[PDB]
Image (cartoon, rainbow, N blue to C red; front, side, top):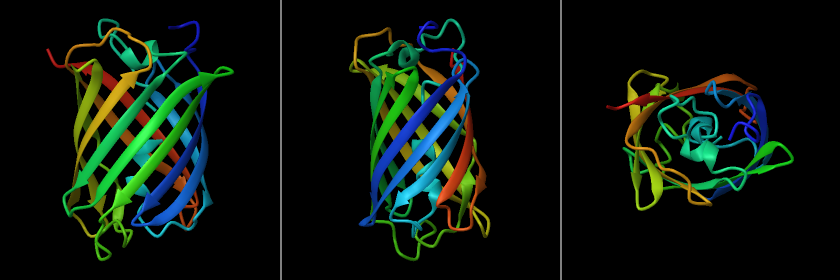
Length: 217
């Protein structure tokens, strides 16, 4: 609760990843306002840089403790701490690309620690991911609902393309507290993720994310 999740909180993130067999590691630190639903992340590619694919397929893997929730929606993921939560995500891209992500979130020495494993497969070589033709995510609405003692989220996520139009991903995430905590009912999280800066080859990236829970009913 509010004792251990403070109004300003830092995080450290490590990602081990493969996309179409290209292995990489990313280390990052972030900060934000967990009750205000805002955070920034500073990522560095530490291995396998420069990435031969669009940064944008990684950007949504770098923090669900920082969602602003109405007082009457139980904040399942904040309540999970200090033990924290795991999440497993599947992203089905419209051209057959697949991203599966597993993530451990915990709290150590007053900081969130994120460990991400990512596998991207079956991106066509002439597709917008491997040709780096993407231009950031549209604002998303994640449909949250409880199921089988976890919180599920579903998103129709849209990547803007440099030449116009959109590249669609269907996303399902299971978020599971490491201890039993109160699950909410159905509700929506409005998410906007921006790349605020990057160097020419995306080995250094800053992101900013606003996420706000809203009532469905």
